[PDB]
Image (cartoon, rainbow over all chains, first blue to last red):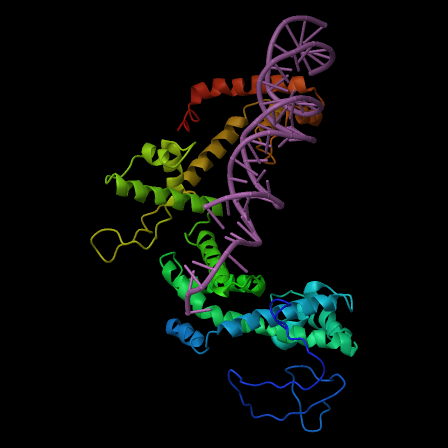
Length: 53
Length: 345
DNA sequence: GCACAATTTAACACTTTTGTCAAG
DNA sequence: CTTGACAAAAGTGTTAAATTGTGCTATACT
């Protein structure tokens, strides 16, 4: 999405998107837990072993 | 030292690249519109959901436990809203997180341009607010420039921010400054006058005159108006100003007390309150009363003829004459005894 | 620094109370 | 000690003038 609707990138048919040439990368010691349908947690609160995300 | 302190604390964070800036304003406004879209969902206020976001972001029960002894109920008007917006479909749910992160970025923006605000208020020293105090009032004038910004205008946030920094600073200096309080426009008009003074004193080389300085000011300005507001210009004087060539002297103690009776004054008012009593005794019983009812010597309040007449049962005309003969009757005894001929100042 | 809503003040038209006079 | 009649003084109500309280602007400037 861009400033003006013109520079906005529109998918030409179907395919796969890939991000390249980052300005910088930042690594964080953490553990990634992907989901599918919504979320029961909220940004910023505390979690514990066994807790349902 | 708080001085170097603030500078180093703001020097703990990098500024922003043009990219970071544009992106900041973007996500910020996406959150601000997200809340607006949430108001159309659960049917709540624009600012309600807004602040309640900070209630889970800006902190735990510390945000609503001290905005004064009263702000808005934390367990009641908020907690119900923290769970009312909690049961919504995936469609509405995301617009919440966009509000949390969106409103979050705002802080980043402020923190970023803070290294600007501090460097702005730097040229304003002398107002009577030492740096940090001066800078602070300016920092809040950043918070205004932020929420009202528009990235779409393709303008560097600097230009928009700076004006709102100077606004806030110039507003605090007219609302604090001098010990006494000065309404804003008038504070400015002072500055305008001095601004002219130091100008035509510069051109003509000799200091101006109350008439010519007002002349160069505009219409309606006269020799008196300038001196008039000039009187109000100057502030009070420190009572701690040492007087004389010594180190043991002050300016405070050199001020008397008129708000309290002097012993001679107590004795004076006593002599009048007494001598008048005995001088009162020599009058007709009805007129002796009516007399102290018309001077407010009884209940401290004065009773008009209408009341006195209703007190005895006579008319408002009779009482009137009663006073005439009363005072004039004590006249004779006073022109003799001369005890009360005094108290003439 | 300025356009202006906000609120205060002096402005003033006018009603009512209160001091007052010649006569009972 | 008493009326009635009046003018001055003190009220009471609505206005015009002024005085004071506020939000804000956009090149960029960290």
